[PDB]
Image: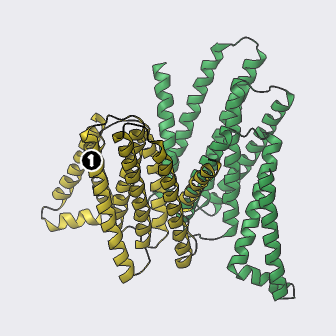
Chain colours: A yellow, B green
Amino acid sequence: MFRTAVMMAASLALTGAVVAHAYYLKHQFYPTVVYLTKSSPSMAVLYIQAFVLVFLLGKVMGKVFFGQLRAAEMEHLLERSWYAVTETCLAFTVFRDDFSPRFVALFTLLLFLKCFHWLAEDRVDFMERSPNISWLFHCRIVSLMFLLGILDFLFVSHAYHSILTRGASVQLVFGFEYAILMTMVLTIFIKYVLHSVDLQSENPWDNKAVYMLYTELFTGFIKVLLYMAFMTIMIKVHTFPLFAIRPMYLAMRQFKKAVTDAIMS
Amino acid sequence: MFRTAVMMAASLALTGAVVAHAYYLKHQFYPTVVYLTKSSPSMAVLYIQAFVLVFLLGKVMGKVFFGQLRAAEMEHLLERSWYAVTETCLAFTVFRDDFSPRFVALFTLLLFLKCFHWLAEDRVDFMERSPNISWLFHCRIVSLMFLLGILDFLFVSHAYHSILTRGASVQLVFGFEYAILMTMVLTIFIKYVLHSVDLQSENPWDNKAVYMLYTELFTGFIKVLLYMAFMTIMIKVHTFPLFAIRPMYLAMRQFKKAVTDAIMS
């Protein structure tokens, strides 16, 4: 993590230089802050420092929960992160609410949770074959599962309250994304308990593995249903969705492959 | 191509039904067309029919120039097509010029040419190893090269004239994208002539292959230079680019890998 430490040190030095420049421009306490908030490049450097701190926190949390593993997990993280960044910015333009740093923070937190969900899926796929099974692995998995579930439930409840009170303007995107994340967490829990039952039973117990596949396909159906409902509401409210069309196609393709595999089997 | 024929027949039937409904609503010639252009779903069906016709023309052109080959070429086409669609819609939001079907047609033509460029790159990579070398292969390659070069030169000249006369509002995006496509066509021409020299000389003639690699890296440098210039102008005109950041990162990563490979060699 030498490169991460170097990057965070560089960002900290840059923000310290910006703060020092502002302070030496206005010796008081209020005008320096108002100049920082009025000048654009200084606020941009502050945003970069905030993003770097978020990245450091994400690295710490990933080391605590999963721990390194530096593999296709990282490649999937990068690919889905680029896709999610494109989708998020698209959905942001989808509405006139530009800038709005609180909404930017909300989107960043959503991206944080989505990246952690993808890493959880990759760790589940690694666990299904031949992991370093121990007490700590189970503890990490259950702790991450409970944390993600609690946070997702709280945020979806807040989104439901917001859309009931204010309306379906921008909070519905968060609601649907966190609903998809809840489906992902349900799939993760099902896969983990199935693998635990398979491991604790010594014998392969294949009669349940097919059932696990059944559960998987059912969950996929649920997911695609949610997505199509999203599409419906997104054509009911505004003109035409643009941000989620590619994820819709991906979900449709995955469900089609799953149902074809189930039929041929 | 059974599925493509079925899809085009379905789209043609749908547009015929829309036309018949409009005609039976207004028996004249002018009000039916004005109702089609005023109603949104009918114009959407017309747009879908236009896209399907464009897809059929693209299939015909691909069969004429490359010919099937149904491989990683198609996978790269799909991936880069999703990426380019996201980038194009992002660039469209980048400006207040919404709808504007002529600009939509221009973007569609740009996507058409970019997809054909990617297929040309994939065919070059296939040709470099062990293709079905013959007169027809050379004819196809040179014809596609000349067509792409002529079209790119004409469109970049038109973009230069537009930005000189009107200004850098939306035509600069087309100019930079077609400049990147021109660099791609230059790389394709260099690779093709290098492979032709390698094949016609019987002996491997490795002393030039390294030179070919040199040319490749040089072209990559040119590409990244163009991209950074794009970034500069895009921060000079408007607030902050959003559409091309991921392609910028991809180009930077490719150039970094190329320069590291050149240094270690």
Q: Nearer the viewer, residue A202 or B212?
A: A202
Give the percent coordinates (x, y) of residue A9: 23, 42
- Residue at 63 percent across and 46 percent down: it is B179
Q: Is residue A95 above or below residue A74?
A: below
Mark 1 belongs to which subunit? A
Q: Is residue B215 above or below residue A192?
A: above
Q: Nearer the viewer, residue A86 or A201?
A: A201
- Residue at 38 percent across and 51 percent down: it is A115
Figure quadrant of residue B208: top right
Q: Nearer the viewer, residue B25 or A154?
A: A154
Q: Say left or right for A226 vs A13.
A: right
Q: How many marks?
A: 1
Give the percent coordinates (x, y) of residue B25: 81, 88
Q: Say left or right for B243 vs A25.
A: right
Q: Is residue B154 above or below residue B137?
A: below
Q: Say left or right for A217 vs A65.
A: right
Q: Could you classify mark 1 by the number of other residues whose Cα lies within 10 Å: few (under 14), some (14-19), or many (20 or more)? A: few
Give the percent coordinates (x, y) of residue B254: 51, 36
Give the percent coordinates (x, y) of residue B110: 67, 54
- Residue at 66 percent across and 70 percent down: it is B100
Q: Amino acid at mark 1?
A: Met
Q: Is residue B87 visible?
A: no
Q: Give the residue at the far left of this rendering.
A: A28
Q: Is residue B4 above or below residue B24?
A: above
Q: Give the residue at the far top of this rendering.
A: B203
Figure quadrant of residue A103: bottom left
* Mark 1 lies on residue: A61
Q: Is residue A123 visible?
A: yes
Q: Label 1: state its secondary structure.
A: helix
